[PDB]
Amino acid sequence: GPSCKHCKDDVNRLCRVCACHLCGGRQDPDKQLMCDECDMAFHIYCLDPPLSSVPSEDEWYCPECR
Amino acid sequence: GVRTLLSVQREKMARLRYMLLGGV
Ligand SMILES: [Zn+2]
Ligand SMILES: [Zn+2]
Ligand SMILES: [Zn+2]
Ligand SMILES: [Zn+2]
Image 1 (tube, rainbow over the protein chains, first blue to last red):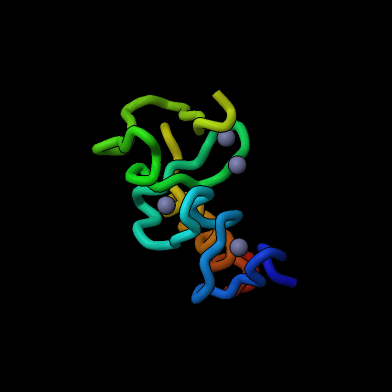
Image 2 (cartoon, rainbow over the protein chains, first blue to last red; image 1 turned 120 degrees about the vertical axis):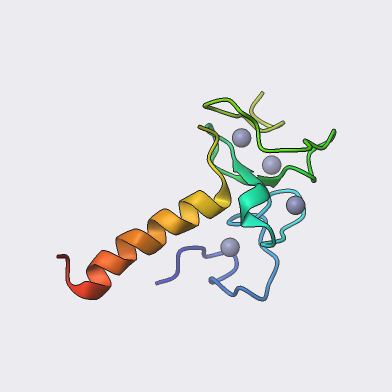
């Protein structure tokens, strides 16, 4: 083999490693930002505070790496 | 540009597509 040992690429399990590091959900992959430091995924609406949109910059860093 | 999970997933799909074919 899989690409994720933690969820064995079971798309019907939550995974905070290859999906949203905060809630684990794989829904709205278009709204899951990839930290340009640790390469985790984050729902814009899981961040505290939530981002109403996908940032307009060239890089983004999650609350754990900033 | 900020990368999304979707963008990353699409790139892996594209890479896979080329090997699915046979690399050309
Ligand atoms: Zn996983
Ligand atoms: Zn989430
Ligand atoms: Zn990070
Ligand atoms: Zn963490």
